[PDB]
Image 1 (cartoon, protein in one colour):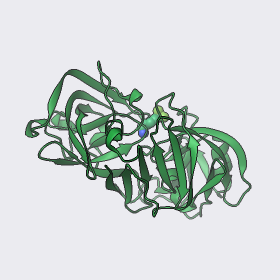
Image 2 (tube, rainbow, N blue to C red):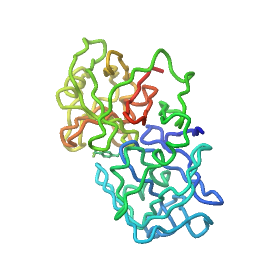
Image 3 (cartoon, rainbow, N blue to C red):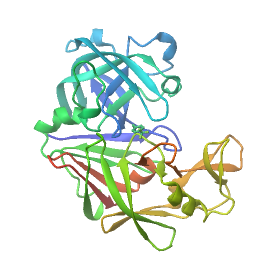
Image 4 (cartoon, protein in one colour):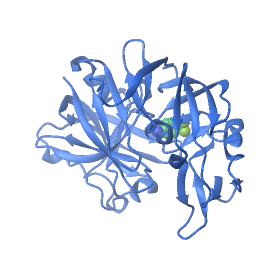
Amino acid sequence: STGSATTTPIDSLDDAYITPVQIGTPAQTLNLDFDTGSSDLWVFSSETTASEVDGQTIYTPSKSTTAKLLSGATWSISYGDGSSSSGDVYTDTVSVGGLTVTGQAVESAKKVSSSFTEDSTIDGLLGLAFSTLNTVSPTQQKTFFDNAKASLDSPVFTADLGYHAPGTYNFGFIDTTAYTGSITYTAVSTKQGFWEWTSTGYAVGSGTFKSTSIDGIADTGTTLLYLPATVVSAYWAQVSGAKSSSSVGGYVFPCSATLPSFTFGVGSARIVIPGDYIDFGPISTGSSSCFGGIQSSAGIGINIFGDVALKAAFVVFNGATTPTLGFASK
Ligand SMILES: NCc1ccc(C(F)(F)F)cc1
């Protein structure tokens, strides 16, 4: 079987993407943020503290004839930006784009941090990293992808994110009309639970390609591109007037400048990020300083190929017994 669903930017900067997901019987449709950097499926629900909910669609397990409380199970998660949430656990039917899993763990938020509450367009997260990162206790739970793997035609999903435009998540098949050229595959380490891979180098604008190993994760759940300080300094040095700002928390640049592209290596292939993708607009309304889409990973501890990078490519997440990541130009 296969599934296919459209994913839509939540705002005009592509800060995140939401995908409709059907939970329960009869279906309750929630717009979830598909996150290959985490492994929990959690939703705003009828059990979330009423003050922590501001326009989200909530899952109501009591209206689902297929929902079952997973007695005694709890979950608690903290994200790399300081976000957190926690609650209890149901199992229920979950469908994405026509692909249905029965008995999926649905983590119901009783508490959410403030940054989820302020984001009225996101009803929850759908984790697509490896199930070893799932936070359910005492019994760890499988991700939607892991549950679906058996019945998929091919154990893969693909991410085709749009620039200021809708895109597609496909499960179980590779759409050979959605990319150009060949797909280059590259090895994945699952030892930390992430889709972790090694990029072979980079170039700034039309400069020479520097061969150098950059280990990092493919994370649809992270907006920006976080790379080592040496790389990020070499990029912003080519933008007149760019500087690292401690009050803003990263590199900013004059909104009037034009940004060079950024190339990253996948084996012998090259993925080019157009400079326009790196502009995240004014730091405050009316400001002439603009926020850069490439930032240093030094304070994070791991390099992250977030949406800025991934939306420049067609990306294959191959969850075969030896996993790989595939990249193609589009
Ligand atoms: N998208 C989920 C996520 C968030 C943060 C991190 C970090 F910061 F731990 F690398 C990984 C994955």
